Image 1 (cartoon, rainbow, N blue to C red):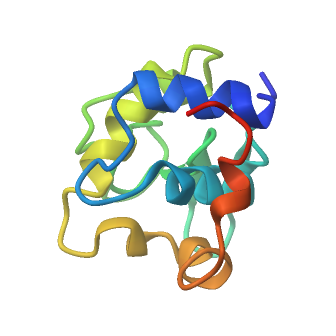
Image 2: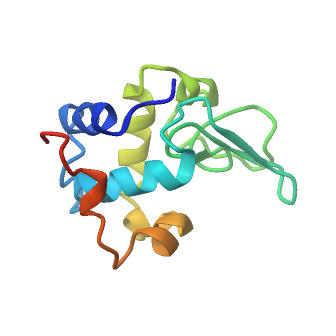
Length: 130
């Protein structure tokens, strides 16, 4: 599923993301835009290290979810990677909450650092009634 911006914004808000661990909803929206373009089916295999990023938030198979083919996988979210490719983003959201509970927080995502951090991200939530 490819979400429309405001549709995703209200969905995240209902899932308790606004201000989660100090992260504003606009930041979460900036991250999903750059990571997947709001597409829940998004997958990116990293040939250099044998891991794959899954879904909307492009969560990694080395530490967060299990796909059975990544060396040293940890499965911290205790989820099959398949769960992060569904139209229902409830699992991806619970897992993304778990990732940010680590020391680095939202900075765990380099893309956040490159395209969101210290930027005017108001536009991601503008007009969504959120």
